[PDB]
Image (tube, rainbow, N blue to C red):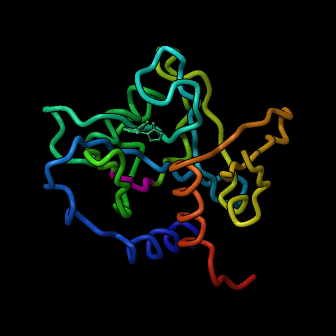
Amino acid sequence: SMLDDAKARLRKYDIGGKYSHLPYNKYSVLLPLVAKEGKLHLLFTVRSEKLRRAPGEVCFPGGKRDPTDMDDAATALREAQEEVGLRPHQVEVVCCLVPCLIDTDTLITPFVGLIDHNFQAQPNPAEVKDVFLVPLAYFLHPQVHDQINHIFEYTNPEDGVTYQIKGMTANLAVLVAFIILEKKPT
Ligand SMILES: COc1ccc(-c2ccccc2N2CCCC2=O)cc1
């Protein structure tokens, strides 16, 4: 099926816990995959202004590891719950993609999660200003703007609202789209 096929593709790129023990300042992000209307979508947040890191920006759910977390996947799930109300029975973590090195002392670990069809986001306004979906296929033919550095613009056909997706977030979106959608019969 569609979801079984996504999982089987994603498992081929799982690095596991290989880089998880190194002595960095550690953050995790959840890349949440949602099936709607026969197709896969990624869920994004718009971060609240009040926040420490990346205020006002489009980002995946995520944040800083704390002493309660059993492992880096636990950080990603804890933070997704706090930001959009995603509960643990509502997500299956399928793999750990290549981590992102930043600022010489920081490592950000991305996890891909399949989201239950009955989940509905409850934006926590202390953390998140907005939550939106983008079809995964968009990232194969995005609308690109140069600010030189590349920025995607996505307009939601439901309401005409435009979002700007850039940086690590845009890079990880393209990666997931390639893994799942490359070389597919129609
Ligand atoms: C919601 O999850 C987050 C958000 C931000 C970060 C983060 C941490 C340290 C240095 C840079 C970081 N990023 C990554 C994108 C832009 C930005 O500021 C990690 C996890």
Side of 167 relative to 70 (left or right): right
Q: Quadrant of residue 173?
A: bottom right
Q: Residue at x 39, y 26 (%)?
A: 82
Q: Residue furthest front?
A: 148
Q: Quadrant of ligand 1?
A: top left
Tell me if residue 50 comes above or below residue 112 in the rendering.
above
Q: Position of residue 110 (x, y in %)?
A: 38, 53
Magenta residue span:
109-113
Q: Residue at x 15, y 43 (%)?
A: 70
Q: Report if residue 111 lies within the magenta region.
A: yes
Side of 85 relative to 144 (left or right): left
Q: Position of residue 130 (x, y in %)?
A: 62, 26
Q: Nearer the viewer, residue 67 or 157?
A: 67
Q: Residue at x 42, y 28 (%)?
A: 53
Q: Quadrant of residue 144?
A: bottom right
Side of 125 relative to 23 (left or right): right
Side of 89 relative to 146 (left or right): left
